[PDB]
Image (cartoon, rainbow, N blue to C red; front, side, top):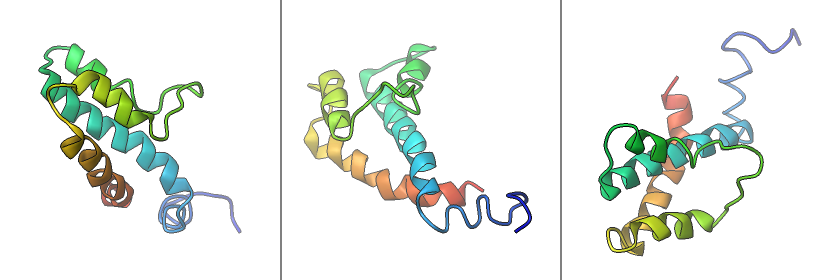
Length: 104
């Protein structure tokens, strides 16, 4: 109507309407799982940071859908089995969704 500006249609509508919210929440949920799993592997310093700060956003050559389960499993074998892995994956799915607006 006017352009896209303000807290009018660019956040407060854009995430009321799904679509845009997917993109944000995806690039949040991965970070929340990464910092969990770093806290299982036992990391400190920048190694813990790096492990949370890799699996999220990435470049346009980082595919997954279900590979996240395998990706984390190949690290957390013998520390955290499916009982937690897919549980956290779900427990952050709807949480990261709502957390988009709740973080405003």
